[PDB]
Image 1: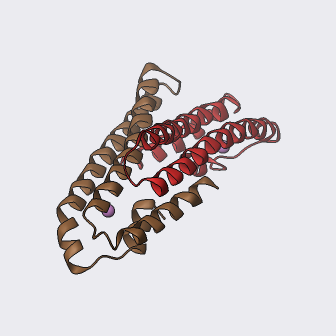
Image 2: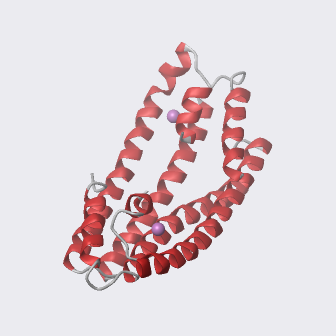
Amino acid sequence: DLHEILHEAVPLDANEREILELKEDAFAQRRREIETRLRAANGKLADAIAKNPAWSPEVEAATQEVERAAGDLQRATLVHVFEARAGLKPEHRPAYDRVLIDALRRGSQ
Amino acid sequence: GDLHEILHEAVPLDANEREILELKEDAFAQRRREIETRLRAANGKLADAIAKNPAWSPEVEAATQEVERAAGDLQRATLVHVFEARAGLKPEHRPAYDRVLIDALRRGSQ
Ligand code: NI
Ligand code: NI
């Protein structure tokens, strides 16, 4: 929810909004792509447990995919934070940082 | 809701099942706190780094990887707990537990 709390947290001029809108679509593609992997991995866990409620090679395999998809989402969200930052004018960025830093510090708790 | 909290609410236990699962539930709860601790420490590491140099530094790359690991750890740790809890259940009560488990998980496939 770092993406959510940062989204529209700082002002944006006309040209900043349009660039950050393109970056948002790129993020949306990557996110939906990871989200699909997560969904498929869950579906296979469903079949596995419904077949045999034990930690089978099926369960382990799907779990690693869930693990990887979970981690990929955290990295993708952080990368987008910096990508969105790079789309700001070199005088607006410190305002973006202060919200980001606090959002992390209040999450360090 | 969370799968751990979906199950905890949806499939109820008897008096004996709760007393039996008490030790294991406390074990998982403290395992979760350890991972939560790791996550918080990772976030403060990112906060301190960006404040020094708002960039993708080695400090940022390392902390992100720590976040990536802890996020994955929680998923596995939760799943292991799900099976551990299932073991301490009466054989008769397991289909209900399984039903909530499979359904809650099936929702995560859509
Ligand atoms: Ni965004
Ligand atoms: Ni539990």
